[PDB]
Image (cartoon, coloured by chain):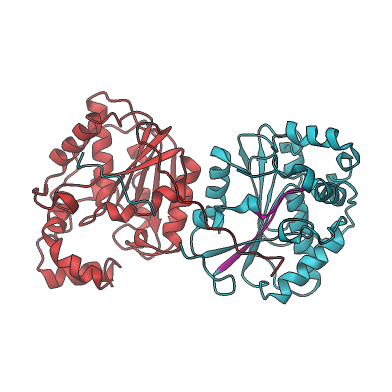
Chain colours: A red, B cyan
Amino acid sequence: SAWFPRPVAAPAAEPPDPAAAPLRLVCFPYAGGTVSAFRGWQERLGDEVAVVPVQLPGRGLRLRERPYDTMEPLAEAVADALEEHRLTHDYALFGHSMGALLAYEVACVLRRRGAPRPRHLFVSGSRAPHLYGDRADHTLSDTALREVIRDLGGLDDTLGAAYFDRRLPVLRADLRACERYDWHPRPPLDCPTTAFSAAADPIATPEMVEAWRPYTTGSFLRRHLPGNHFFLNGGPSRDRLLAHLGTEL
Amino acid sequence: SAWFPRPVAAAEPPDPAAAPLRLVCFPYAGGTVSAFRGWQERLGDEVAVVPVQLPGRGLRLRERPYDTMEPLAEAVADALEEHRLTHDYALFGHSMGALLAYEVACVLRRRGAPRPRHLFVSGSRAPHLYGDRADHTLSDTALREVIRDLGGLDTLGAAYFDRRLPVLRADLRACERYDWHPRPPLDCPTTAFSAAADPIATPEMVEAWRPYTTGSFLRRHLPGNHFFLNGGPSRDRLLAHLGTEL
């Protein structure tokens, strides 16, 4: 129709230099995940935030390297890397699930080292840190661990089915840092925190996500999204998460 | 370094008739659907962005433009029904486009059509506060300087000003000669957007939208001038805010 012309396609984008970016958003994947979980994010947030996803060792082009199964050496390796590339200034942290727990721990570790503190902390699909330890799913078989991820919405793809087998070590090593973790009591963070729950998620229920509140002194908001533990892959709530991020950034 | 590989630069736009939601968008005075370029990409695939091209511009350049808000409202409503876009929709409008959106909503309810899921109004005073100005009467250079000073000249406004001067006048007439005829409040939730450096649509004037709906009202304040929609931090913020309610 003359009234409703179809919009012209957005011209392909030159992504900002993480050095030359007003803000940098440091993104942590879920257990068994890679940097592809944050495919498309740069486009959806614009040019005032450079999206810098973190690829842990044991996956992608780091398949030959050994994955960590212990949370604090990992958190310490991560902070080393950040300090070694001047990212710990005008920056914030996103983590989903294991990435959330990992995000928090790296936050603490940069405080102890007296690194310039973060602007914001985002955590989705993750219970409060003190609540981590009771599950032991990294000790399962494969078919059990497959079905657990399936019932949480992690794999239905069938391409994924292929990639699942291959990344089982790295999953197990990711999940072990979450279940052998027990929260060393420590003070609260001064930065502001935003936590995302999902309605169809058992592993991060509202009350569990609510439990993050006393983990910080600054402003705390719990947004509540629809969908499951794995909403982040695609759908209406991945879109909403991204829009909420855009408002606080 | 291997910790931070630079991601791969990332689109098939959903069918208006299929999508779970339509977001019908109205530009400001003497603006085109160009102001909504980039939107679909930023808002995702659960919503089909449907910019509305009013007569008088773009490929409609030689069609005669509407310059009264009510007949414009009726033509638009006819176009929306005729193309089966009257279900699962929301309206957005910046400045003049907000008023058009509000009036279109009112026409649709009158006709029995299903009501919109949301009404988004940006950079616009409340309906009854329209009618005080006379920018559409100014001389060519005078009017140019007004819009130039409000931040309204990429977009091609600057490039295609003289060519658009006739639709600028017509669009501004429809706002500046508008006298709100009483009707009941809408029922749909409504977000209103105002900008900190905007002398034309101040917070006081934007807050006044509140009683025009029985649903919930939220105002979001953002940095920049009257034409904040066009680019920059303020545009991103606007899109993100839109995201959270669609």
Task: Indicate yes or no whether the magenta region holds residue B24.
Answer: yes
Total labels drawn: 0
Residue B93 percent across, percent down from the top left: 70, 53
Task: Indicate yes or no whether the magenta region holds residue B215.
Answer: no
Q: Is residue B27 left or right of residue A133?
A: right
Res. B201 image quadrant? top right
| Location of the N terminus of chain B (image quadrant) | top left
Q: What are the residue bounds of the magenta stretch?
A: B21-33
Res. A94 image quadrant? top left
Residue B154 or residue B126, whichever sits in front: B154
Q: Is residue A226 above or below residue A156?
A: above
Residue B78 percent across, percent down from the top left: 78, 72
Residue found 69% across the figure and 70% down from its top: A1
Residue A130 percent across, percent down from the top left: 24, 45
Residue found 52% across the figure and 48% down from its top: B240
Res. A225 in view: no
Q: Is residue B224 above or below residue B59?
A: above
